[PDB]
Structure formats: structure tokens, C-alpha cells
RNA sequence: UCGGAGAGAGGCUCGGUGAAAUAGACAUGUCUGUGAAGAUGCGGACUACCUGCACCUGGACAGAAAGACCCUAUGAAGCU
RNA sequence: CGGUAGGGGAGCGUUCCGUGUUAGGGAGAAACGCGUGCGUGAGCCGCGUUGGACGAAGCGGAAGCGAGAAUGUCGGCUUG
RNA sequence: GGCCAGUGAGACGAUGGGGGAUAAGCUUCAUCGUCGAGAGGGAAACAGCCCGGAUCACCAGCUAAGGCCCCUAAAUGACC
RNA sequence: AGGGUGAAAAGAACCCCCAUCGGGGAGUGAAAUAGAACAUGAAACCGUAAGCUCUCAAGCAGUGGGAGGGGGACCAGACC
């Protein structure tokens, strides 16, 4: 359970950039919702 | 059983390369006839 | 595994889920338009369609089951005097699940219930 | 603006033609062009090949006919061409070798009792998967893995023998589908096959 | 310095973590003020709102300090750095105590108008270099 | 503080293409040295020598700067058509050379350490080398061996 | 008589500057910068003696591969048979260099070794 | 035997806050052999595209903690 | 003219002191960072759109005088 | 002799033996070789086995031990 | 345990973002990259931009050779 050693700058920038790329994937969805929130007949967002 | 395995440095007196051919021990290096001595490596020219 | 278990259970235990259903469909029948989460929205949709069509046939037995389900006294008797005059000929589909922005603090998918 | 990428790309190719020089092949070639004696001292250092010396387009192509040829000496003389140790341009760090083609893999001779006693066993990672498999079983089943197993242990199994492993083209049929560079037959120096 | 093109806006050590500010700041890089205006209206992050406050107070800065428009204005770099980290000695069981660090950011966002010349043709002229200083202000692949 | 402007001198671009196409390419001819080639033996090691080349070698025992020095220990002198295979030295041979100023080459850090037996030695070595420029090769017109 | 100093940082900054392009904490982290200076210098030793040995090996196999292109069984050993019997003192395996820079001249070498 | 289903709190995902023991640097395969006699690091062969997520803990002689057992100290102390 | 435990000889560096209110220095000292330079090396010398007031060499002396290790120790910041 | 240190745990290999079971990479001695304190080459790897004693440079040559099919330098060398 | 903005608070009038904190102009100053966390600011650590390069690959991450590519260049063969 206890880690034997530490990680490099290598593997850490890989994992942190996979985390922040996983943050990248959930804003073109927000760009699509922000673009559909604009002028148009949409039956949502009262 | 009663046969001892040959361990390290007894493995080396047994399994080292030994050239046990009485011909190939007799070999000396080849002899070419002697040549005259080569001239000077360079010369002062004034 | 959940093959074909079509009950929609929330993040609450069973009796607390029943009280959430009864209270939120009660105040849904009080105000008409309401802000829920989407799980709470569909969970309101089934039961409030059951309560619109329950007092559609305004007998005493339907009125007593309907008064037994809903908390408030004076809202069941404001219901069967309203649902045959309004929701006759609709034949199902008494609500609308207009969604909105997520909630600040949870990113909870937040919905909004009509009566149409 | 497609003309930015296209026209500036062709300007970069244009100054690639103007600044840089081509690399002449090593055939009927003297020591130096008079430009080359002004350039680097490529004489007193060991000759190292450039990218225009090991192009896979103008490599040689060899065809042996493995009918009644013994396996291991054929594998060694295919290896000595698959490295490039019959060329004076041999550098053991680049791919100076030559493509070879081995037709008739189904009729490869062996000497002694190889056919019933030599095993091509293999194993996956889990225990109890060691596959009992003898020479006649592959030669009945897939013969072009025989020679392909013989020469794969003849090449330096790093990143570079793995690259010249694909130069081997073994086919079990009597005819190979290659008409690449008109493949000249392979020269042998083995008097005992 | 780009000859008077960019607008640099710094930020206080705001009371949140640097890494989530770096995913929300690595989203909005390269996109202009309208797209970040509509995305940061609706991004589901708590680190979204001071970033949107600094973009809004950065382009309003770019329209009041300079005199630009909020449509031809792309985010240039938007770098987020570390700040001061507080230390919180929080007790935990079996007589132990853990340092819980309260992290702060340091946001510096640079904005970029397009103040262009848009020359007619490409063809090089190796004459009058004291005009070649002014005619070429921001291009690519500088030879010699 | 503004975008600067368009500048209006009303220029006309010269598209004659007889000045820029003269300016951008360069005409530089290599000097034709001659069609000759030797292999000298200096110290112990042999050098490919062509007339005009800034070679490096060993001699710093004694040799004055800018001196005119004949390297008469020549084997395998070769022209464009024929070479002269040297039974050891080609006779009456003379590679005329210019021994130039003496140099020290790059540092070769000879640092030795064994293991935990705590021993380490940083020493350095500047080899006393000599750069030689080559003038021309002569005295080589005996026993041709062209093929 | 306090003696706080800076000489460990110049002592250490020189070794820091030598350890460039060492791929990670061998290029940044001081307590490995030292042992990569050390192991890099002994790597320079053994690879220098074995670059003498290794280029000897490379010229041997290069001129062997040049001589074996005749087809008739003339090995590299027989080229030295009739390279020292016909008295050519010590061409120093630079005929493996002009064997590719001047292949007609090495054909003149070998074709005069035959005669 | 011989398990099976269901309800909660965790676990999984999202949004907030956010540690810890550990850590020479880690570009951190399997078999087999060798070696301070139990090797990802040495040798030969075979096998493996890179990198995550969720579980399991066989190894890293895993973490702890200058072995309570054994012995040594011209050690300490209690007791007889 | 390999070298552990170890012995001897010769040197570099640091801060202060004598020369010294030294030469030099807001026309940029010390610092910090840099080298296509020199040394057997400890190091010197030179260059800096950074910095802003001190301080060399030579000939000498004195040390809280040189760091990679002490489950060292004190601050800073990582890993997980 | 003067001044002044370490070391006093050794290990394997050949021979001469004792203890053992003429068992142990076992234990104790006597002469010697190596390692310790010894790099390089051969021994696949591998302190003690063979050659061999590393001041340094060379993109120099000849050899010892050992090798000359390929991986990997040199003979798919010759004759019994 | 926590010292040092300037020489002098001359400590930022006024405009914009704006609930503040903060930020940008302007103004003071020789210096505002001396802005109150304020004097030189190094390493670990976290980043962003530019050049080359990694997704059939076994490696104490080097070193010797160096394919291909990039940069300034002047002893254009050199250097990184």
C-alpha cells in the first residue's frame, strides 16, 4: 500500500495532463450548450 | 549420491578454455625477412 | 446487476424516498412549476401522472386514496375540481421536463417541471 | 491562404535545392569532386554512410532456390547478405543489407535426424503451455517458418536486426510474387551443401 | 514586446488551487473573447468564475486602457503560476498532526488584438531596411 | 496610441527579375588543386594527403612555425588515372608541406575511479599537436601500375 | 568567526553545467549530478580505449568485405599473406578507407598484390 | 453442504475542499543461468504499441521500528 | 610512474588582518549568471539590456577554512 | 637506529597433512599464486582459474592466453 | 519564529473592470519589471513560448561513432 519510491517529472506530467485533457473534453460540450443557448427555439432553459 | 558439484573457481579450473592440442601450443608468430630502415619522418628545407 | 428493475431509486433509502415523492409531488401540485433534479423530475413524472389520472374519475374511493397519498388536506379538494375541466381529452402526458443550468456547488443536472 | 503553405513550402524546397547538395553514389566514383575537398575531412575519419547510401529503393534483391539445400548453412549465407557484410560499405549501425527471397521452403534438406528429433518448441507466459512441436510438424504445417526461425537467430536481435528481419521474403511455393528490381540469383561461397 | 500589441493583466493570489485553475485556463487558450465569454458563462467549475472575472476585467481593460474591440481579441498565453500556500496544522487520531496547505494561484493573462497591415503580395525586396523595420511587425519564418 | 497606419508613398514593385535573381544565387568556384593523392606516414600513423589540407599531427619535438617541410615518407601516391603502389616507400618522393603554428587539442579529462574503495583522480591531457598545410606532391614518376 | 561561503555553489555549478542532456533528474538533481559527472568521465575512458579497439574491428571487417567481392576464394588472411610477402610496410588498415573512397585504386592495390 | 436475493454506509462517476505513511534517480518484462549461494538493473533466449481507469495482492528479500527471541558488552537495572 | 588501511612532499580556494584611506569602482565593486580561453586539478582570467557600493593582485599571517552521506539538523518544495 | 602509522575477522586454487564420512564455497595448519589493494583480454554472464601488470594521448602496428559459420573480429583453410 | 521600498511616502489625484481583494492606464520617483507579500533573488519546485525528436519499445538512462534536421555565423572544414 505504501509507495516504494516516487514518480518522475515524466510520469507526473503525463498523468496530470491526462487529468487536464479530461478537463478539456467537457467544454466543447459546454461550447455546444452555450451555442444552443443562443437565439433559437429550444424547449429548455426557462 | 555422493558426487560434489564443482562450485566457483573450481568451475573456473574445469570449464575455462584450454587449448589441449599439442600442435597449437607449438605455434610461434610468423617471421618475415627484415627490411631496410625507413627514412626520416621529415626534413628541414630552407 | 439491474436487469429490468424499473423502479427509479434515488440517493435516499426507501421510506425517505417515499416521503420525497409525496412531498415533492404535493408541492408540485401546489405551485405547478417547480425546480428539481432530473432524477427527482422523472420520479415526479410517474407519480404525478398517477395523481392527475387518479382523481380524473372523481369518486370517493379515488378521492380517499388520493387524499391518502398527498400530504396537504386542501390541495386534494382543489385537484378534482380542476383536473376534469383542464386535463380532459389530454389522455396522458401531463407534465414537461424543461431542463436548466446545473446547480452551483454540485454540478447537479437540474430540471424544471411544468404542468402541460 | 493555401498559397502560404504551398508557395513558402516550394520556396523552402527551392532553397533546399540551392543551399544543399546531393549525395553521389559509390559507382565508378573517384575520390572527390573539387567542392568536396573544400568541405569536411571525410578521409582521415572513418567513412559513415549518409541517407542517400542506404536507400531501400536501390538495394539488391536475391533469390535462392531452397530445393535440396541444407538449412543452417543456407541460413548463414542468407545472413551474411542480410547484414551487408559482402559490401565494402558495411557499417554495423545502419541498414546496409540486401533483400533476399527464398522460394521452395517446403523442400529444405537437413542432415542426420533433424526431421524427427529437432523441436521448435514455444511457450506463452503461463505455465504448462510449452508447445511440443517437431520439424516435420512445421514442414507439414507451415514450412516458411522453418527458414524464418533459422535466420532470425543469425541477425542481431536489437532494433536493427528487427528492421532487417523484414528484408527476408520466404515463400513456400515454386513462384514468388516479386518483380521489384529483377532479382539476381544469390552468390554462394559454400562448397558443402 | 511585439511593438504595442498585447495587454498583460496580473491577478491576486486568489483562494483556490493552482491545478484546477490550470485545467480551466488551459481550456480557454487560443480562443477569442466571444468564445471564452460564452464558455466561461457555462463551464461547470468553481475555478471558472475568477478566470471569467479576469478575462472580463482584462478585455474591458483592453478597451479602456487601449481602444480596441471585444471581437477581434484572442487570448495570447494565459499563464497561471503558484502563489503563497498557507499551512494548517490539523490534528488526526493516534496523536498525529497533518499539514493541510491552503493553496493560492497567481494568474497572468495576456490578450492580443490583430493590428495588421495585410500586405498585398509576398515578393521580397532587399532594399530600404529602415522601411523593412516598420513594414514587418509580426510575421513567421524569419530568414537572415 | 493606435494601429499605426497604412503608409502611402505610392511604391511600385520592380518585377524585372534581373536584379534579385542576380543577387540571391552566388557563383563560387572551387580552386582546382590537381589530380594527385598520397598517403604519408607521420609518427606511426598514416594520413590521406591531398595538396592543400589543414591536417593535424603529432610533431612538437621541434619544428619552427611557417616552415617549409618535405614529408618524404610516402607510400601509395596516386593520380586520377594511375596510382603507384609503394613497395614500402615510393623512391625520391616529396610531399611538400608547410608546418604551421603549433596547437594544443581539446581537453581529454582522464578521471579514474575504481569503486567504494575510495579513489578518484581528475587529471587532464592537452596533446601537443601540430597543424600542417600541404603544398604539392612531387617525385613520383617511377613504376606505374594502372589498371 | 563565522565562515558562511559560496564556493560549494561554483564547485557545484560547474558540475551542474557539465551535466546537460542527461534526461531528467540526472540533469537537474545535484546528488545525482555528481555521480553522472563521475560515471560520464569513466564512460569516456573505456569508450576511448574501445574506440581504438572498435575502429580496428570496423576496418578489419570492412576490408574483409571489400576483398571477398572477388568471388574466388581469396580471404582476408591471404591478402595479408601476399601483403607482407610483397614488401608493403604497414598500410595501417587505411586501405579499408581508400577501399571505399577509391575502389579502383584498391583494385590496383589488390591487382598488384596478385602479380 | 452451497451458496442466493434484497435494503442502507462506503466503494464507481461528477462539482467543491483536500492529506498521509513512503521515496537515491528511475526509460521499473518472463524464463533460465550466474552472482554475497532467492536479479526489472549481469548473460542468452522468448515475449511485449503508448498510456489510463476499476479490482486482486504474488514480488519489489514491500512500509514500520537501530529484532522483544540468540550471542557479544570486563554494559544498566530489579530481585535472591 | 595500478593501488585499499596508511606515510611523506607540493599547491588551489574561502573570510579577516599588515601593506591599505592599495590599484580599481554609479563611465558599475561584491553578488548572480555566462564561456569556441588557460591549468595535473583544486581554480584563474574574460564577457553579461540582471544588480547597485565596495574592494583586487603581489608579498605574508590566522582560522567556527572547503559537504554527498551521520534513521544528521533547520527552512523551502516535491511524490503518493 | 630516530620520528611515526595502520594491521592483528582473511578468501579461494595447487601440493603436504590432521578433524569429517580423504563430504562440504567445511575447519585448522606448512610452502606458493591471485584477490584483498588489480584495471584489461579470455572464461556467455561471474573476486581468487589462464594470459597479463593500466602515467597519458593516437580513427597507429605486432602478439600472449584464447579463437577464425552467423549473432560477434579473424579460415564454410589444407591433409590424415 | 518572523530584519532591510525609497534619498525623501514624494504610499498612486483622476478614468475603467468592480461587492471587495486585486489589475491596467495616468501621476511621483533616477528606478513602479523599488508598489507596500515592496532592497540583490540562487537551487529544489511549478509553469508558458521557440528548435529537434519519441507511440514494435527492454533501459543506473551515460559514453564512443553519428543518420536526418535546426541556429547563428568567419578563420565558411569550425561552434552549439
Image: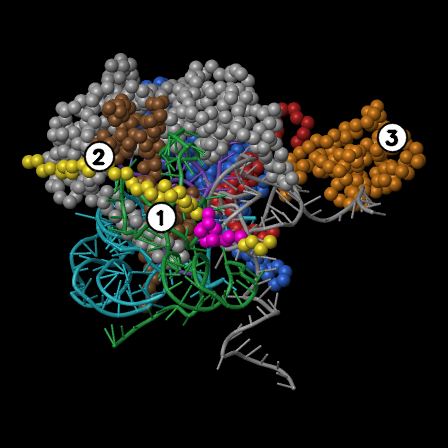
Chain colours: A red, B yellow, C orange, E blue, G brown, I cyan, J green, K purple
The numbered mark at residue C56 is 3
Where residue I40 appears, x then y in whole percent? 26, 52
Q: Residue furthest left?
A: B46
Where disc 3 sits, the SS reads loop
Give how far apart the Cα atoms at labels 1 and 3 are: 95 Å
Pointer 3 local density, CA inside 10 Å: few below 14, some 14–19, many at least 20: many
Residue that badge 1 annotates:
G42
Chain letter for mark 2: G
Q: Chief secondary structure of the magenta span?
A: loop
The residue at the point 64 percent across, 37 percent down is: D129
Residue C11 lies in the magenta-colored region: no
Numbered disc in front, either 2 or 3 = 2
Which of disc 1 and disc 2 is earlier in sequence? 1
Mark 1 chain: G
Asked which secondary structure carries label 2, the reply is loop
In this view, the residue in front, K66 or I75, is K66
Which quadrant of the figure has residue J63?
A: top left
Q: Nearer the viewer, mark 1 or mark 3?
A: 1
Mark 2 → mark 3, Cα distance in angstroms: 120 Å
Describe residue G99's horizontal placement relative to residue C32 as left or right: left
Residue F38: tell me if it is visible.
Answer: no
Q: Magenta includes B8? A: yes
Horizontal relation, residue C40 to residue G29: left or right: right
Left or right: D166, with G67 as reference point: right
Residue E64 placement (x, y as % from top left): 44, 35
Q: Which residue is mark 2?
A: G89
Above or below — where is I48 with respect to E123? below
Q: Secondary structure at mark 1?
A: helix
Distance, label 2 to label 1, CA atoms, is 36 Å
Amino acid at each position: 500500500a505504501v509507495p516504494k519510491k516516487r514518480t518522475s517529472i515524466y510520469k507526473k506530467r503525463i498523468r496530470k495532463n491526462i487529468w487536464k485533457k479530461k478537463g478539456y473534453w467537457a467544454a466543447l460540450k459546454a461550447f455546444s450548450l452555450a451555442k444552443s443557448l443562443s437565439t433559437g427555439n429550444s424547449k429548455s432553459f426557462f | 549420491s555422493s558426487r560434489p558439484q564443482k562450485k566457483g573457481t573450481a568451475h573456473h579450473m574445469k570449464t575455462r578454455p584450454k587449448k589441449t592440442a599439442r600442435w597449437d601450443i607449438k605455434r610461434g608468430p610468423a617471421v618475415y625477412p627484415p627490411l631496410p630502415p625507413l627514412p626520416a619522418e621529415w626534413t628541414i628545407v630552407s | 446487476m439491474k436487469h429490468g428493475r424499473k423502479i427509479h431509486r434515488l440517493s435516499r433509502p426507501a421510506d425517505q424516498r417515499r416521503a420525497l415523492l409525496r412531498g415533492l409531488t404535493t408541492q408540485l401540485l401546489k405551485h405547478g412549476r417547480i425546480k428539481t433534479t432530473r432524477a427527482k423530475a422523472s420520479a415526479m413524472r410517474k407519480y404525478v401522472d398517477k395523481m392527475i389520472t387518479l382523481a380524473k374519475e372523481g369518486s370517493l374511493h379515488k378521492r380517499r386514496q388520493a387524499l391518502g397519498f398527498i400530504y396537504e388536506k386542501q390541495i386534494v379538494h382543489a385537484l378534482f375540481a380542476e383536473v376534469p375541466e383542464r386535463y380532459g381529452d389530454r389522455n396522458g402526458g401531463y407534465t414537461r421536463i424543461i431542463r436548466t443550468l446545473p446547480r452551483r456547488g454540485d454540478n447537479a443536472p437540474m430540471a424544471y417541471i411544468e404542468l402541460v | 491562404s493555401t498559397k502560404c503553405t504551398e508557395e513558402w513550402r516550394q520556396l523552402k524546397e527551392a532553397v533546399k535545392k540551392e543551399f544543399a547538395i546531393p549525395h553521389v553514389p559509390l559507382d565508378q566514383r573517384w575520390m572527390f569532386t573539387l567542392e568536396e575537398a573544400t568541405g569536411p575531412d571525410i578521409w582521415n575519419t572513418t567513412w559513415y554512410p549518409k541517407s542517400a547510401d542506404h536507400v531501400p529503393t536501390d538495394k539488391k534483391w536475391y533469390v535462392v532456390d531452397a530445393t535440396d539445400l541444407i538449412l543452417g548453412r543456407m541460413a548463414s549465407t542468407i545472413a551474411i547478405h542480410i547484414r551487408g557484410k559482402n559490401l565494402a560499405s558495411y557499417t554495423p549501425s545502419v541498414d546496409m543489407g540486401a533483400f533476399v527471397i527464398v522460394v521452395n521452403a517446403d523442400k529444405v534438406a537437413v542432415s542426420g535426424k533433424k526431421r524427427t528429433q529437432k523441436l521448435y518448441r514455444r511457450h506463452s507466459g503461463r505455465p504448462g503451455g510449452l508447445k511440443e512441436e517437431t520439424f516435420d510438424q512445421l514442414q507439414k504445417r507451415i514450412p516458411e517458418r522453418i527458414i524464418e526461425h533459422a535466420v532470425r537467430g543469425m541477425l542481431p536481435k536489437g532494433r536493427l536486426g528487427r528492421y532487417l528481419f523484414n528484408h527476408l521474403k520466404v515463400y513456400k511455393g515454386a513462384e514468388h510474387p516479386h518483380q521489384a528490381q529483377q532479382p539476381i540469383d544469390l552468390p554462394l561461397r559454400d562448397k558443402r551443401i | 514586446p511585439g511593438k504595442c500589441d498585447e495587454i498583460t493583466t496580473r491577478g491576486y493570489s486568489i483562494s483556490m488551487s493552482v491545478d484546477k485553475a490550470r485545467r480551466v485556463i488551459d481550456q480557454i487558450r487560443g480562443r477569442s473573447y466571444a468564445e471564452t465569454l460564452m464558455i466561461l458563462e457555462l463551464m461547470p467549475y468553481r475555478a471558472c468564475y475568477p478566470i471569467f472575472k479576469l478575462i472580463y476585467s482584462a478585455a474591458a481593460n483592453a478597451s479602456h486602457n487601449k481602444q480596441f474591440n471585444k471581437a477581434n481579441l484572442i487570448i495570447s498565453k494565459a499563464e497561471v503560476n503558484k502563489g503563497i500556500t498557507l499551512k494548517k496544522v490539523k490534528p488526526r487520531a493516534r496523536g498525529r498532526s497533518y499539514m493541510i496547505k491552503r493553496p493560492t494561484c497567481h494568474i497572468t493573462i495576456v490578450l492580443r488584438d490583430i493590428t495588421h497591415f495585410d500586405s498585398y503580395d509576398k515578393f521580397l525586396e532587399s532594399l530600404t531596411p529602415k522601411k523593412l523595420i516598420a513594414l514587418l511587425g509580426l510575421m513567421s519564418t524569419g530568414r537572415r | 496610441v493606435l494601429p499605426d497606419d497604412f503608409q502611402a508613398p505610392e511604391p511600385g514593385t520592380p518585377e524585372y527579375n534581373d536584379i534579385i535573381n542576380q543577387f540571391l544565387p552566388k557563383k563560387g568556384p572551387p580552386p582546382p588543386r590537381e589530380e594527385i593523392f598520397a598517403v604519408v606516414v607521420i609518427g606511426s600513423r598514416q594520413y590521406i594527403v591531398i595538396p592543400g589540407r589543414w591536417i593535424y599531427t603529432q610533431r612538437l619535438k621541434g619544428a619552427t612555425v611557417n616552415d617549409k617541410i618535405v614529408l618524404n615518407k610516402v607510400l601509395l601516391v596516386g593520380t586520377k588515372a594511375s596510382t603507384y603502389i609503394g613497395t614500402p616507400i615510393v623512391t625520391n618522393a616529396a610531399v611538400h608541406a608547410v608546418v604551421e603554428e603549433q596547437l594544443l587539442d581539446d581537453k581529454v579529462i582522464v578521471f579514474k575511479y575504481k569503486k567504494k574503495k575510495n579513489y578518484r583522480r581528475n587529471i587532464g591531457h592537452r596533446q601537443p599537436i601540430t597543424r600542417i598545410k600541404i603544398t604539392g606532391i612531387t617525385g613520383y614518376e617511377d613504376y606505374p601500375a594502372s589498371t | 568567526r563565522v565562515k558562511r561561503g559560496y564556493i560549494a555553489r561554483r564547485r557545484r555549478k560547474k558540475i551542474r553545467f557539465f551535466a546537460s542532456s542527461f534526461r531528467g533528474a540526472h540533469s537537474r538533481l545535484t546528488r545525482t549530478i555528481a555521480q553522472q559527472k563521475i560515471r560520464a568521465l569513466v564512460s569516456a575512458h573505456r569508450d576511448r580505449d574501445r574506440q581504438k579497439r572498435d575502429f580496428r574491428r570496423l576496418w578489419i571487417t570492412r576490408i574483409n568485405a571489400a576483398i571477398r567481392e572477388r568471388g574466388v576464394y581469396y580471404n582476408y588472411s591471404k591478402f595479408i599473406h601476399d601483403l607482407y610477402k610483397r614488401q608493403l610496410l604497414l598500410n595501417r588498415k587505411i586501405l579499408a578507407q581508400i577501399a571505399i573512397l577509391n575502389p579502383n585504386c584498391i583494385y590496383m592495390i589488390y591487382n598488384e598484390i596478385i602479380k
